[PDB]
Amino acid sequence: ATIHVDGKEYEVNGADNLLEACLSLGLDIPYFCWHPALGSVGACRQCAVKQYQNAEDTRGRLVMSCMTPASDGTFISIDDEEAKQFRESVVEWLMTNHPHDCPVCEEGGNCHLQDMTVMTGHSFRRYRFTKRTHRNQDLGPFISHEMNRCIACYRCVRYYKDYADGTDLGVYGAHDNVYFGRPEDGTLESEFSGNLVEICPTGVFTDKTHSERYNRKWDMQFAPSI
Amino acid sequence: VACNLCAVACPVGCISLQKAETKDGRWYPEFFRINFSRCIFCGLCEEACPTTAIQLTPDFEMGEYKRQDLVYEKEDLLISGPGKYPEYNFYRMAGMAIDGKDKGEAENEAKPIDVKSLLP
Amino acid sequence: AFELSAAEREAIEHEMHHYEDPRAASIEALKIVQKQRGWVPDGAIHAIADVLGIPASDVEGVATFYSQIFRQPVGRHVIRYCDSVVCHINGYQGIQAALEKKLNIKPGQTTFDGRFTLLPTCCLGNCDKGPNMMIDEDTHAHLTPEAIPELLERYK
Amino acid sequence: IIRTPETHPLTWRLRDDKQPVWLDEYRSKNGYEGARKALTGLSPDEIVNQVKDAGLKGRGGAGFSTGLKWSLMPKDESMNIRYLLCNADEMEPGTYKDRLLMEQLPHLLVEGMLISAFALKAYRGYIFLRGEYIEAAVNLRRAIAEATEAGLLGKNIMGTGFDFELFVHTGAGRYICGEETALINSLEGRRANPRSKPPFPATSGAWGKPTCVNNVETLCNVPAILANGVEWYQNISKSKDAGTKLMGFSGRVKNPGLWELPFGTTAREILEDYAGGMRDGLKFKAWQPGGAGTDFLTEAHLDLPMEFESIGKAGSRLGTALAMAVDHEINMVSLVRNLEEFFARESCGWCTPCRDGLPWSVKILRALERGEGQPGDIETLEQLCRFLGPGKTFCAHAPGAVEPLQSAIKYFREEFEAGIKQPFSNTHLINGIQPNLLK
Amino acid sequence: ELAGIKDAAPDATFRIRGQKLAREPHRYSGRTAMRANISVHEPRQPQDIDTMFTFSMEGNNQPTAHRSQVPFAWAPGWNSPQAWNKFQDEVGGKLRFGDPGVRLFETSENGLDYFTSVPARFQPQDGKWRIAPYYHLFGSDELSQRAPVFQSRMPQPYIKLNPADAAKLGVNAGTRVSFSYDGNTVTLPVEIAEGLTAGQVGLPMGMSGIAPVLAGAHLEDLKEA
Ligand SMILES: NC(=O)C1=CN([C@@H]2O[C@H](COP(=O)(O)OP(=O)(O)OC[C@H]3O[C@@H](n4cnc5c(N)ncnc54)[C@H](O)[C@@H]3O)[C@@H](O)[C@H]2O)C=CC1
Ligand SMILES: Cc1cc2nc3c(=O)[nH]c(=O)nc-3n(C[C@H](O)[C@H](O)[C@H](O)COP(=O)(O)O)c2cc1C
Ligand code: SF4
Ligand code: SF4
Ligand code: SF4
Ligand code: SF4
Ligand code: SF4
Ligand code: FES
Ligand code: FES
């Protein structure tokens, strides 16, 4: 397939969507709800790019790159001004309820939400009202729960239920009061519940064993082991 | 709150700390040590503190006989008052619950609404 | 704990006969339990989940998504006053103020005797006869603040 | 108003005492004759094509061609399981047409679902009805029992070998459940989050099977087409939209109600000749043509025919064609605050712009209500209007949420600017730190 | 037969444009103070003669570097686990220059013969109890069950009994029964297992006191303590 991103021609796979095709080419599009192992559901509305009907088109429309296929002869723009403003607006809406928690959060320096906040160029807050609060649950000795940091990207429920076939983690409530977790306090019953600490782009589900003796990612000595 | 921003913002790398936690959930440094034989007194650590805990004070008289005694620990750094910033409290800003401050008690924070609430 | 009665379980199974997936009867199962017991207690979620064959997280998410399935204890009579735009034009606010004055409660809570629970609600579909109120199964239209204590005394 | 079968195909059977019309009275007044014609003398594809060239558009508020939506069901013969769903939700503020249709004429809806299920080869049908229409639910269940007793429902209807089972699914009170994909999800017993299209419900809808979702009024319009013929339906009015629409006018008018009118009837004809004008002491200020989700229009737009195209080019939508009148005594900012409060609390929480930006608009309008507005608030509201438009959110809840906000800013900006009093302040002073006085 | 382990990873002389592979990130902190409690003189950097990696940041961790062993994923602007997107040839696929590790053996050209040794059916003999293995993700592995965070997650030690076998032994759920294996009478509480077949007791393999060598073995004098 042939796509044109910002006037540059690329050869992609027509069976992929535009987000995974453009991320495979090294282009940077912010995203939250899409995962390579989970698929595209179009929740966070963050991966917006401007699609044009043909080469001689100037108007276009904002579409989700994760929901739009990477078909042949597809003209899109990532660095368009309207798309950039919309992505910064999505980060701004996610920043309205987010707690002032980065120093005391175990995802600091390892946070996908921090990365996409910086990448969108959003560093000014014109929101002056209150932020919603949630009480935490006890998820057992491995996963620490902090629901204030959630951005409702639905990755945890999608992985835990649709991928890992777990039953004890879900989504409750409606509007901006959506809550993610167990119906009551107790240990997460899945054998693959620890992948939530990397599935969650925020610091909601965190490693409690690492949180006991915590240090940031830049302070680690890593090795490739088995 | 042992957030390790000052240690990584240091261009010399003369700040070492480890995060401990109280039973009520408050982060603090288990130890905090600064190699003052290495420190260039540039103030990037004070610039990087989001709680204004680390502070460079107007005092220069710091000569030492042995270089081992130029490694100041937490018992030699922690003072009895707020220093140059007399009112800032990070935990009032934060949404994490600690002792004496529950959910919704932070500034610009609403009270937590349960999903089981009868209101639409 | 919680135990599902025979009538509730029989009604739930009869509702499961109406669909090709038993999960489709979760909303009506919660409605059956709420009709019998006034609300849905915490053990009812697990009982309904065990009966239908779906996880309790799904049942709790359904019961918390919809506003008419109550996961907190309510009064004997649920007053639901419409606060939408047409009833805002026709003056629902005087009706709401009369309800506060008579019941001595805010919206979303219950009286001291457990008689009434006052709730704002969406558009009741009766906008040409507004303002509208809905006590448990009876809808009242053409509301005036002078008629609220006359309306509330007939619900024991 | 004189109601004839040729001019009022829907409401000419309505009783004077507002009582429901049961099976014997309905069949006396030419009931189930269209169902008899369709099920005995017509192929399902013939009925689909008949509805398609009748010009029957969807009365749910979008105006899509119902016959074209019927034709998009697959022709594959392995998919012999098909569903017809009646969107009896009606959760839009300002909409009360289906309550009148089902509370007094449930057999019209039963006959319409029977004809449409024969046309769509739909073996099962569900009336997704809201939980607050108790009388409509009772009357629909009684009409279904009466039709099942007389052989209009169940197995082997009219000796044609067509089996159709009709159920009534009573809802649990959410406005998002009226969205047809969220309607399918709530019919499946799940949280009523909508689904992305394509795939549309025709190819894969309820439980992955082919599924057609239609409003009460469309299925009520169907048997008149199947009984009186196509040519009667095309010559009801000389307009691009065929047939009669239930149009009403509500909100502090002399005669608030609902009347069956041909398409192309002007809104001033509804407001004055049918609603009797505004109440005494109240002057007309604005109106919404088709419910809470449509844009406000002024008194200059009252001389406009109520069609999809005419209200579309005027900066609004025809919608459900149940107009609402706002007088001068009602503040515009309070009305938009109420609308946005409803639209924000009825968000399903699936996607970021609606879920996290409608409460921001609610907070801004609350600040503008008590005069606590600050500079940049109306600019923020305009940015939310631009960024919550069609294609930017997952479903069409938020475009309908920001339509009244953008129209009220466009036409009544002097009321919104009157709420901005204090200067902008997001920070507090921290002792020992000099602020960055940006310019 | 282990000739393929040479190609599992490149040797200690492997370089990326002359430099080694960094173990720690470039922004590694506290170099002159993490060991200052012991000695203010900073120690020598540890030497890694075994591998191509180095015990410092003085190395390469570029996502476009021609290697298969990646110690951690970091790209500028991607500090999250989403830097693996930068480290892959396509997202969700393989690594850019191949995944590490090699297969020791290929598929053989010829198969095996049919195993004609069909076992007989399980006959539950009285007085002897066949041990059915129960494996736990938290407790069966030796090193993992030595971890203190597993101790709350480990199940309490048990013996599983069929309802018919428990009724024959006259024991309900929770009571403690003793059984002797190689002269070690160990006492465990009874849990009723409906799915377990009669004539069998279920034991948690890999636990403290219950070796995995006990699986498939028999038991004697099982009785209520
Ligand atoms: N209570 C009520 O009556 C309410 C009505 N509405 C109205 O609902 C409308 C928005 O609803 P939507 O579902 O978003 O409208 P839509 O235009 O996306 O679709 C409406 C119908 O057309 C069909 N359709 C549209 N494009 C199609 C295509 N390319 N292929 C196949 N089928 C297609 C859909 O399947 C559906 O049956 C607005 O006009 C609004 O006024 C909104 C809120 C409440
Ligand atoms: C947020 C939202 C709510 C809706 N609510 C209803 C509703 O309550 N009743 C209805 O008939 N259509 C509703 N619709 C329109 C449906 O998407 C769809 O048009 C309808 O179910 C059938 O279309 P039709 O008019 O062609 O029959 C809603 C749409 C949206 C976006
Ligand atoms: S989840 Fe991310 S943005 Fe939120 S407090 Fe933690 S590090 Fe900061
Ligand atoms: S808890 Fe984490 S993974 Fe789940 S929706 Fe919230 S941000 Fe996404
Ligand atoms: S003032 Fe000293 S300790 Fe602080 S960043 Fe500079 S060199 Fe490091
Ligand atoms: S002194 Fe400040 S910057 Fe350093 S770890 Fe403590 S809170 Fe963080
Ligand atoms: S716009 Fe988004 S969050 Fe709002 S109701 Fe639709 S899908 Fe749900
Ligand atoms: S990544 Fe596309 S909307 Fe979330
Ligand atoms: S606006 Fe209140 S009944 Fe519709």
Image (tube, coloured by chain):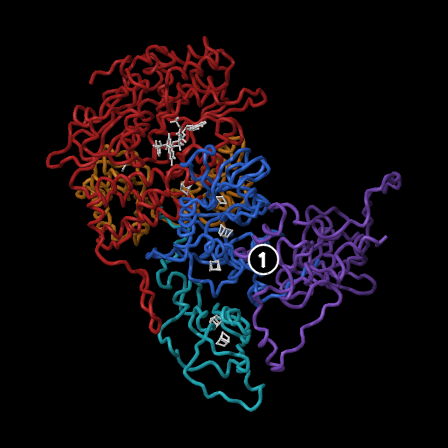
Chain colours: A blue, B cyan, C orange, D red, E purple
Q: Where is residue E177 in the image (x, y as percent from the top left)?
A: 72, 60
Q: In which quarter of the image is residue B106?
A: bottom left
Q: Where is residue D324 in the image (x, y as percent from the top left)?
A: 24, 33
Three-letter code for the amino acid on which mark 1 is drawn: Trp
Q: Position of residue A173 (x, y in %)?
A: 43, 47
C155 sits left or right of D113 in the view: left
> Which residue, given by chain and number where applicable, does mark 1 sit on?
E74
Q: Which residue is drawn at 51% across and 74% down?
A: B29
Is E120 placed above or below B91 here? above
Q: Mark 1 lies on which chain?
A: E
Asked if residue B46 can be seen in this view, the reply is yes
Number of callouts in the render? 1
From this viewpoint, which residue is outermost toward the top? D41
- The image quadrant where one finds the C terminus of chain E is bottom right
Q: Which residue is drawn at 42% across and 10% down?
A: D37
D369 sits left or right of D132 in the view: left
Q: Which residue is drawn at 54% across and 44% down?
A: A22
Is B37 placed above or below A89 here? below
Asked if residue B22 can be seen in this view, the reply is no
> For ligand 1, which image quadrant applies?
top left
> Between D6 and E134, which is closer to the camera in this rendering?
D6
> Between D302 and A174, which is closer to the camera in this rendering?
D302
